[PDB]
């Protein structure tokens, strides 16, 4: 059948970036309402266009557990869940 011990993908969380390094190729988010820091990088940002995070920045995201069993943060947006213009576009 369909495993559903969670929301069926990545459960919503909030936090603040520990650091986003494009050189290292990895970053981490400290979840404000969670425990373990979640891995975050460009491919986990809510942006399909311009996707990058600022080290000290606060964020709202979904936390998804990677195949390494380490939970990672994706669909990263502002702390209020506010989308950035670089997410896709919009026009306004």
Image: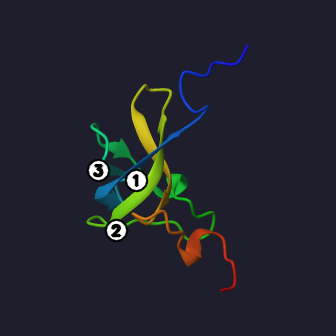
Residue 57 image point, x, y percent: 31, 67
First of labels 1, 3 by sequence position: 1
Residue at numbered disc 1: 25
* Residue at image location 63% in from the left, 18% down from the top: 3
Question: Which of the pair 43/90 is nearer the observer?
Answer: 90
Residue at numbered disc 3: 32
Q: Quadrant of residue 87?
A: bottom right
Dot 3: few (<14), some (14–19), or many (≥20) neighbours within 10 Å? some
Mark 2–mark 1 distance (CA, rounded to whole Å): 14 Å
Residue at numbered disc 2: 54
Quarter of the picture containing the N terminus is top right
Residue 91 image point, x, y percent: 69, 84
Q: Are marks 2 and 1 in contact (CB under 8 Å)?
A: no
Quarter of the picture containing the C terminus is bottom right
| Viewer-side label of 3, 2 | 3
Residue 50 image point, x, y percent: 56, 71
Question: Which of the pair 6/52 is nearer the observer?
Answer: 6
First of labels 3, 2 by sequence position: 3
* Residue at image location 52% in from the left, 66% down from the top: 51
Name the outermost residue toward the right.
Answer: 1
Q: Are marks 3 and 2 in contact (CB under 8 Å)?
A: no
Mark 3–mark 2 distance (CA, rounded to whole Å): 16 Å
Mark 1–mark 3 distance (CA, rounded to whole Å): 23 Å
* Residue at image location 53% in from the left, 39% down from the top: 10
User: Disc 3 on helix, strand or loop?
Assistant: loop
């Amino acid at each position: 059948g369909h495993m559903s011990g969670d929301n069926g993908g990545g459960e919503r969380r909030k936090g603040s970036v520990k650091w986003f390094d494009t050189q290292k190729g990895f970053g981490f988010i400290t979840p404000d309402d969670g425990g373990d820091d979640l891995f975050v990088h460009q491919s986990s940002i809510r942006s399909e266009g311009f996707r990058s995070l600022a080290a000290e920045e606060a964020v709202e995201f979904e936390v998804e557990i990677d195949n390494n069993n380490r939970p990672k943060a994706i669909d990263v947006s502002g702390p209020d869940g506010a989308p950035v213009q670089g997410n896709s576009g919009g026009g306004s």
